[PDB]
Image (cartoon, rainbow, N blue to C red; front, side):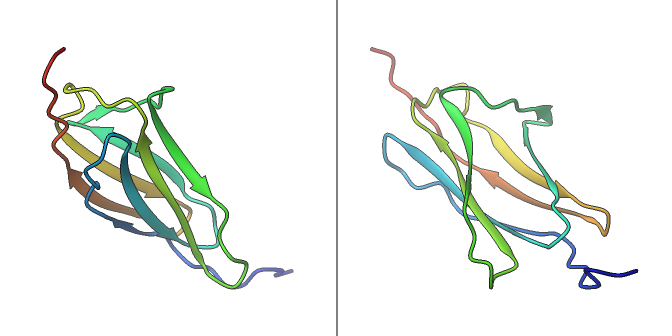
Length: 107
C-alpha cells in the first residue's frame, strides 16, 4: 500500500540576491512530495516572465533538497521590493522572505 512512506514536508531556504547584472536569488526547498513553488512579490502574485524566471535545477537523487534560483536576466527597478517564496505540499507550506534592491538608473 505504501511505496513512499517517507513524507518529507517542504522547508524553504532563501538566499540573499547576489548583485550582478544577472541577479540570482538562490533557493533550496526540500521534500519528497513536490511542493508548488510560488513567488509573492509585495503581497502580489509574481508571475514569471522571460526576464524574471524560476530555475529548477536537477537535484541529486540522494538529497531531498530541490535547488534553484530566481534569476533575473534583465532586472527592472519595479522589482525593487519584497520577494517571498511559498512552497506548499500535502504535509505543509513553508515560506521564506527575500527583500532585494533592484535599483536602476534609467538610461
